[PDB]
Length: 267
Ligand SMILES: CC(=O)N[C@H]1[C@H](O[C@H]2[C@@H](O)[C@@H](CO)O[C@H](O[C@@H]3[C@H](O)[C@@H](O)[C@H](O[C@H]4[C@H](O)[C@@H](O)[C@H](O)O[C@@H]4CO)O[C@@H]3CO)[C@@H]2O)O[C@H](CO)[C@H](O)[C@@H]1O
Ligand SMILES: *[C@@H]1O[C@H](CO)[C@@H](O[C@@H]2O[C@H](CO)[C@@H](O)[C@H](O)[C@H]2NC(C)=O)[C@H](O)[C@H]1NC(C)=O
Ligand SMILES: O=c1ccn([C@@H]2O[C@H](COP(=O)(O)OP(=O)(O)O)[C@@H](O)[C@H]2O)c(=O)[nH]1
Ligand SMILES: *[C@@H]1O[C@H](CO[C@@H]2O[C@@H](C)[C@@H](O)[C@@H](O)[C@@H]2O)[C@@H](O)[C@H](O)[C@H]1NC(C)=O
Ligand SMILES: [Mn+2]
Image (cartoon, rainbow, N blue to C red):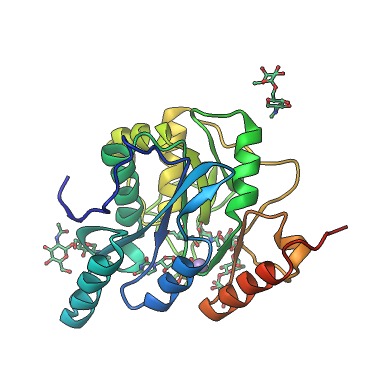
């Protein structure tokens, strides 16, 4: 479907249990390298395969274009299509990832769309998913159930009435990190063209899920996704799935902390 870059992976041969799709700008190489050394490292988690890919569009900068071309050649984990990669095109970026799952990895049991300024505890996520007994039409994350369109003209999430004309948004999950069973990717790509467009990608996916009659559900009896960020501790971070507001160096320091304290017990 018009992909400029496709990861060197074969999901039919080796169906992944969890596929991470990470959004990042071309200049955010430091982010991607920190993820590649930390929670993005492909591995078997409780015998389940984890795969990690980075979603990119295109840019006017020839330098960044060449950098990203070289990165794809060294890492082979970039999914790319020809759309201008800017904040207000994040919906295209998300739909590219969903399209990739639909076309090339329908075998994925679960797919997590995540941001680059994030800590992800794949071990705990896998444990909770294996416990949920939900393999189809499943969608979870930080649930946002009574959200009102931001009508402040200079806010990053401002939508005019012509862009979104209704008083409330549909149920949706924060775009920081959301997880869905792999079949969900095909149903969304299908109805995508008939659902009203909105430039906020997490609201757009919510509109698609609503059209599909897919209901959001909490992953666990306790909160596990933290779009607002968290005060760090080893024992807390062992029992969460996702935390936002995390810069590259902090992610390496947190990952080192968890490695250093492996084998220590927590209340
Ligand atoms: C991370 C996330 O979920 N982003 C979504 C954004 O979620 C925000 C939304 O729910 C609002 C509505 O009450 O609450 C939180 O945001 C607060 C403010 O409403 C929001 O404007 C502000 O954002 C910036 C603010 O405009 C500036 O004045 C300030 O200087 O900087 C703020 C940060 O950049 O943030 C506060 C607390 O974060 C939620 O975070 O909602 C949109 C839809 O409107 C979309 O779903 C995003 O995914
Ligand atoms: C999102 O990406 C699309 C595709 O790259 C942009 O649309 C193109 O915009 C360029 C100028 O930036 C035009 O020359 C093309 O004719 C457009 N093509 C298509 C197919 O749309 C779009 O401008 C980007 N959105 C934002 C907000 O930057
Ligand atoms: O052109 C852009 C701008 C942003 N992002 C990604 O979009 C996510 C959210 O952007 P940011 O963290 O700046 O904003 P937030 O929504 O957290 O306030 C991050 O993964 C960014 O790397 C992207 O892929 N391309
Ligand atoms: C998930 O399932 C676990 C295993 O239970 C067995 O399989 C499930 C699918 C049911 O058929 C159940 O009756 C069987 O005993 C349960 O231990 C666990 O509680 C389940 N978790 C949830 C979310 O209920
Ligand atoms: Mn962010």
